[PDB]
Length: 204
Length: 201
Ligand SMILES: Nc1ncnc2c1ncn2[C@@H]1O[C@@H]2COP(=O)(O)O[C@H]2[C@H]1O
Ligand SMILES: Nc1ncnc2c1ncn2[C@@H]1O[C@@H]2COP(=O)(O)O[C@H]2[C@H]1O
Image (cartoon, rainbow over all chains, first blue to last red; front, side, top):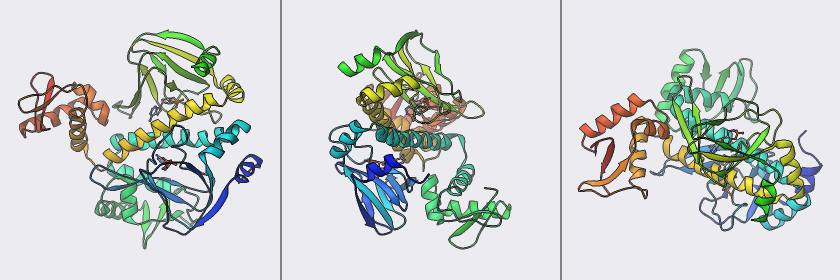
């Protein structure tokens, strides 16, 4: 189901706010004191390497918590930027108020922690993929994963997505021009087709 | 610490010699662990069995937590004792009951999951754009940046073999060997013995 009494009980203690596409909701390095929850829309989580190249860590969607990593220890800073990808409606609540809720009904912490565990798995797998997959394998895996994001439109030949070469590069950790060359190959190999800011993935 | 005591008194604690596999990747997850004493390595590997260490965990760390929140999860990684270990253990089902009495125990587990997410994301962002040379270089450069470093005429000095490097980055032993040799021939490092001087800093 989309939601449930526990989530709605939780949401009743929150203020829900709207953000236009491309808003930065969370800035890296700032003090964390607030927990968020996506009621509609999607965001990208961003970090940088030591040279200041931007990497897209994750997409997060409706039903996902954000800003949860500061909850657990005093005086923590936001680990990453979070930017709207889509017009967003986002519930929000102070860590203070959320800690009470946790005592009232620990399941709400269970819900949150299920997401942190999944994130650690997913993020660990990407790490492994740096070393175990080659760049072509990583782009291809990325196309496969994008293909089952909840925003992926349906098509006679498989899932259609919309993403720039730039964005694919930032997800995988390679340049825009490398993505360019590789997509060209992939479709010349009739595994995908790519006309527009928009790509059809066969199978999925 | 009243809460850890309480939690431990509901576990069974066992001893494992250095080098035991505590957790096997792919196996069905139903049990939670907690390191009472000792250190462990958390590892993944490809179809060739190139290993990559995701992390070390130490005394006071939970392990095998990631299957707790959904039925029928498999273990995401191998976990291997690095020293001799004393490891407490508890069924997920009984850990769920403890969480009902005192959610603070889940606060402590989740705090660690958050620290691990932060560390692992950092490594990903820091390595993703590098090739295997970059990643071996940065690794060396980072040990020059830690406490275990001696000084030198030419720069910082470090101890570590080719296996150990292969693990930080994900690559074979022969590949590390080739790249250390290149780096040496390009006079960025010296391999005097099976230790390494990193020229700079
Ligand atoms: N590896 C990741 N995967 C998914 N989301 C993340 C990841 N790293 C950080 N975030 C999110 O981005 C947020 C940045 O602010 P916090 O660290 O408070 O909480 C963080 C998480 O909600
Ligand atoms: N990136 C990581 N950092 C630290 N520990 C991890 C990481 N990935 C997996 N683990 C630990 O390794 C365990 C393997 O079994 P589980 O997936 O049950 O729980 C996992 C975590 O306890």
